[PDB]
Image (cartoon, rainbow, N blue to C red; front, side, top):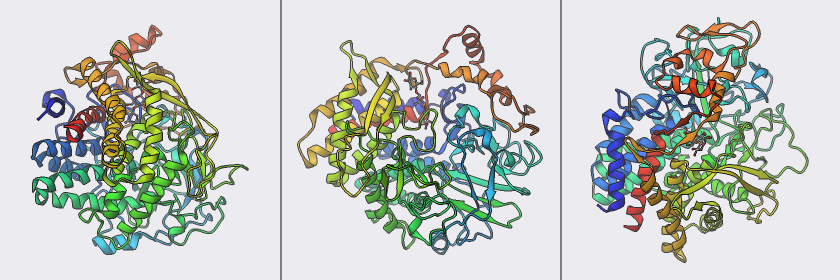
Length: 627
Ligand SMILES: OC[C@H]1O[C@@H](O[C@H]2[C@H](O)[C@@H](O)[C@H](O[C@H]3[C@H](O)[C@@H](O)[C@H](O)O[C@@H]3CO)O[C@@H]2CO)[C@H](O)[C@@H](O)[C@@H]1O
């Protein structure tokens, strides 16, 4: 084991050291060691399917370096036990594939919700349902719900029991301007035990009456990451003569991939390009965009009177995963058991690669994405809108303030997967896409003379690509700008990881790009030199946005009154902290308050679980490819 594999082991040891507190008492990883953090989850001991996917990934690499596949198996075991809803959590009955859901608009601001159901709006057909049921013999949807309250901090428990750990919750529901600060956290299982008279439902969806019900939301990027990780575990185990220990677990990734196809469809199964909410619904695959959209979701009445499934009309390049798609399409170990699963993934692979290329800026960074539902209401695109198989270009799909593609992180996370795919296949389009993007990366990363480094933090965009017709035009009017710089260590490591796979590819298939290998190695070494600490690695970050703890009003309709499980009153006027008063018991609360009352930006050195994973994985990757 070389220097870099040893680097992985040390961080792995930190991560798995019970005293460091990366995991709860059940072995579920938290979002971060530190509880006082707000960014996508709003509390550090929540967890995400993202974290679970990174957990699978870390252990897959451990198996590679180690020959020991127990960690990978227990990772998967935990994932399936807690993060995928069980038969009891999702008792789906009376699903209609010809009427998968009923439509509701999306609106520009949270104060426009609850969104009214519109019962006359045509909805298309779900062509997956029957095939899946036939294949698996079950109505259970095999995907991770995205958000978990690991230690029941909020207090909803499981299935409304108020007590259990590993509690399913949700937050984001109120359109493109509901920031992490502007949500009302609510249980996935709704029995009206909390909130108002109709639980939390009528903050979000307006109906004539309300039924007790469950609903879950998949984050397609996380499920695909897990599949991606399992692909590598599969080839690594095979290399060692250990495939058989893992076989039933590659089967988990295969089945997860089978259900992940829901991410490939328009929200309400409307035809691509329809631009009319009153247009008739699609009849099958005419509503598939074949990309990994922002979510899929599914729900059911507790009494079993009905159920529903939706995809998403909004697609971000940051979610795509050609490695997982390739694996599911082409690798005989990974192919889903359904008749059309592998075929659908072959279509998605090609469509994804076209999407990346279509979105590539004049400089080389990848632009945001596209939607099949302009303003989330199937409206007519403005004149001159660039399109991709009938979908409209959006610089910032889904979230507009701040825009979802203003975060540099997606460049790394997503291009890392393309880089893997190119390494595996030599795909010329991926190679060309990566070469331009690497060129851009090399031009914006700062390797300072004094041994420090900075990576882009925030990006800004202007123009649009040329409408897609199968060939990259150079997109000379689509521009990126680096707004500012930071030392996000998770993203730094991810970026190193992508650069290394690309480099290994060019050696295997073209002219070895040594410069890319060296850029990555520098990032990994300068980081190792500078940022190690007791629990792993961390870099200081000021979080001036944390004034929103105290200042951010949460929209609540006039006259609507409810309560959180801890007794916090939910009504018009409440602040972020008013519906989360347990935050006041946080060890770092005095620090936050002192910073705030003194008008100063509090400063943190966080250990985010995914970030520590990316660091560990990136170092191991150098060993694996250049060892
Ligand atoms: O939603 C995408 C993922 O975001 C992750 O958090 C990021 C925050 O969104 C981002 O604002 C923050 O940026 C830091 C940066 O790390 C730091 O170097 C700089 O000094 O300050 C910025 C804060 O203004 O970084 C993190 C990126 O890790 C979540 O961790 C993740 O769950 C989520 O998917």
